[PDB]
Length: 110
Image 1 (cartoon, rainbow, N blue to C red):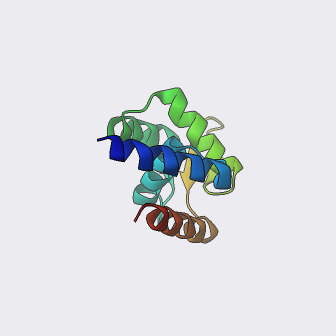
Image 2: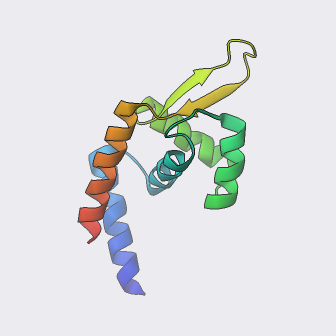
C-alpha cells in the first residue's frame, strides 16, 4: 500500500528532474504509441480516446500533448485543407526517444 506510494513518488521525482515530464505526460505518451506509431491520428479523435482510457480532462490532455510536442517527443501536422484540423503522430526519432524513455522507466522501477 504505502509501498506503491514510495515507488510512485520516486518515479515522479526522477522523471521530472531528468525529463521535465510529469506522469500524466508519460501516460499520454504511452497512449500515443498505441495510436500513432504508424499512422497520424486526428487530435480530436485522440482526445476522445485518451479521456476515456486515462480518465483525464480535456485541458490536462492538451497541456500534456503540447508539452510532449514542445519537448520533441511527439509530432504534429495540420490539414492543408482545414486550418482547424490538427493531427499528431510519432516519427522514427520520436519512437527511438520513446523506447529510450520507457527502458529508463522500467529499470528505475524493477
